[PDB]
Image (cartoon, rainbow, N blue to C red; front, top):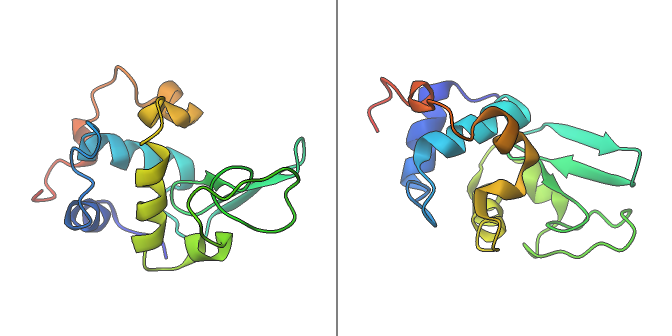
Length: 130
């Protein structure tokens, strides 16, 4: 499913992402935008290390979910990577919350640093009623 901007903003708010571990809703929106373009079925293979990024937040198979074909992988979210490709994003959200419980926080995603950090992210939630 490809979410429309405000639809996703309201969904994330209902799932308790606003201010989770100090991260504002607009930061989560900026992250989803640049990682997958709000596409839940987005997948990207990293030929360089044999890992794959899955879902709306592009969580990596080496650390977060299990796909069985990634060498030396852990499964911190305790989920099959298939769960991150559903139209219902509850599991992808539960996993993203797990990612930020680690010291790096939102910085765990390189794209957040390049595209969202130190910027005016208000645009991502403006007019959505959240």
